[PDB]
Length: 62
Image (cartoon, rainbow, N blue to C red; front, side, top):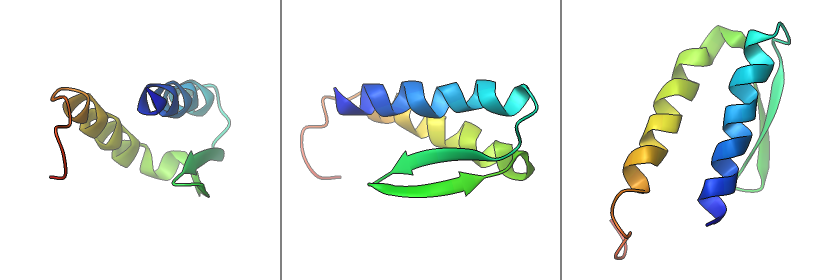
């Protein structure tokens, strides 16, 4: 699925933030945003939100 790919991307970011590079780019909704290690916690919560969304077969709207 597409979300599966968007996950490997935000993940490749956790590796780019622990290697020293503080600024990182992320494609979200066709819109780019630059988070710095200053807010690496929100990235941890966002990822988790995807593991819960890939649980149910979506079914339909919320």
